[PDB]
Structures are given as C-alpha cells and as structure tokens.
Length: 34
Image (tube, rainbow, N blue to C red; front, top):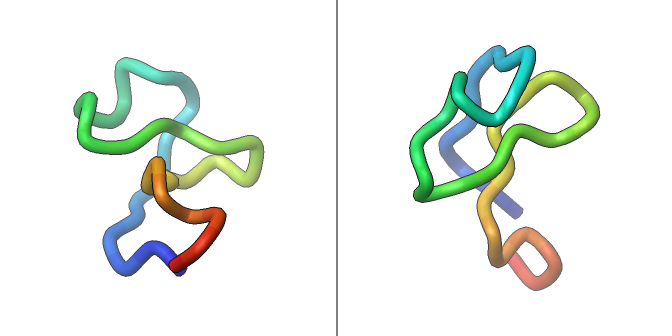
C-alpha cells in the first residue's frame, strides 16, 4: 500500500515516482503489493 499520495487531476500533478490514479491521488507503481 502506497504511503505517499496527494490530490491530482492528471499525470502532471505527480512526479514520475508514481502515477495519478482514478481516485484523484498519487499511486505508487508497486501498489499491487504494498
């Protein structure tokens, strides 16, 4: 489960360290595990 997350309305809203999910928050690439 991702520890760092913030409001986002697109990809640009978050650095390439993660990706903006559908819930409007940053989601870590390895979310499907932690």
